[PDB]
Length: 5
Length: 5
Length: 236
Length: 236
Ligand SMILES: *CC(=O)NCC1CCN(C(=O)C2(Nc3ccc(Cl)cc3)CCCCC2)CC1
Ligand SMILES: *CC(=O)NCC1CCN(C(=O)C2(Nc3ccc(Cl)cc3)CCCCC2)CC1
Ligand SMILES: [Mg+2]
Ligand SMILES: [Mg+2]
Ligand SMILES: [Mg+2]
Ligand SMILES: [Mg+2]
Ligand SMILES: [Mg+2]
Ligand SMILES: [Mg+2]
Image (cartoon, rainbow over the protein chains, first blue to last red):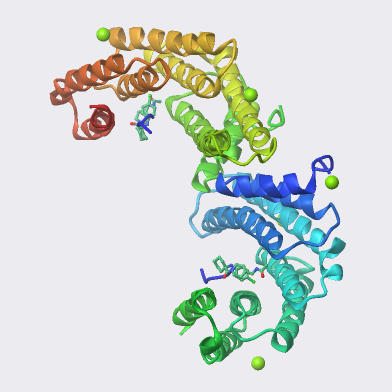
């Protein structure tokens, strides 16, 4: 799962 | 903190 | 009961799904619903009940400790007065914790313990009763603190008496009970020598019984024995 | 509003305590109460709001994924029929997630976005609006899925247009917006080339602006730039 902020 | 189960 | 319309088997199935999803509040509510169907619990079901509430109250206890530490610091010399908020929020978490403990104790009293006739079930539930009175004792500061502590002690002691009569020294329930009663002595009853004696005797008696066990039973028993040793290393 | 009787400042103080205790549901409720006082939020307060709901919905999303995976497996060929429980419980978690998303979107619509006139606040809130429509899109399967996706896209796009006009390429809000809009393209809009182009262009334009920054601003910006690079490595 890709990075988000 | 000591171990409990 | 918000779970009153769900099938017992469906509640147990959803408790297992909730565990897999680490949704422990849901897990606990499902298992409370299952208990309230009124049938005795199997071993697997007893484990689901205990895992659920252990995780819920464990998180509450961790939060209470963080907040109590901040509150203690706020009342040191030279600390800036910051109003009632830290106390208020510690009290909020505390009340929620006490509510969870009262819920579990209520399930044990109505009516799990009285219907539990086999040693393994009765000891397991009495251990839980000692555990949840112990968590109440951790936050108790008033008129009933001594009575709460004695309620924990009494439940643990009844469990201990049954376990020594009816289970082998390596039985994981007997071991886990002793582990937790030893912590009760150290952390709640101000009895570190009793805590150490209980942990050491439990460990040594279990060591001498390992030869009777299968490989899988040996793995179960030695895991808890290592927890006894871990505590002894902390305390000595 | 259950927080309607608590002072704004006390709600903010308790949100910070809740964060320290990792009580994110409480944190979110305190910050919802603070928003509903009607005053604009400072930068620190915007961060508290976003951290709270990010953690709440992040846990819901993780649980939904576990349950959706179990449900998918249950509908493979040769899987034993186990009744409605997996679907029911996935639906329960899904509905709770949708409720949290609707709550956050409600705060943004009533009335955080319309009162936000500075670029940093307006972009931050529009990014949040894109994020919570994106989480709704992750679980959407019906008539409105396309409209939910377009609502996310529209909010992100407005935020992007403001950020490119009004903030430097290293601004952490601009970087975080681009990171998340890029993920939107990859995971929601079925547009991996757009996702890669956006992440790469954002990274390169930020690289060329690092020379203008202090040591502390450099640390902030390069942390998010590494997240852009991490995603690019995943996708290429
Ligand atoms: C139905 C029943 O008899 N349950 C007792 C199991 C014994 C094996 N076991 C464990 O060893 C661990 N947990 C517990 C929990 C409660 C008690 Cl009284 C003993 C042991 C030990 C710690 C790690 C998790 C399993 C599970 C329960
Ligand atoms: C009030 C305000 O301007 N907040 C933006 C801050 C920028 C610095 N920062 C971060 O770098 C981290 N979190 C976020 C969150 C949202 C956005 Cl749009 C950007 C960055 C980056 C990930 C690790 C936590 C801090 C906090 C917010
Ligand atoms: Mg039935
Ligand atoms: Mg109190
Ligand atoms: Mg003795
Ligand atoms: Mg006021
Ligand atoms: Mg649905
Ligand atoms: Mg472009």
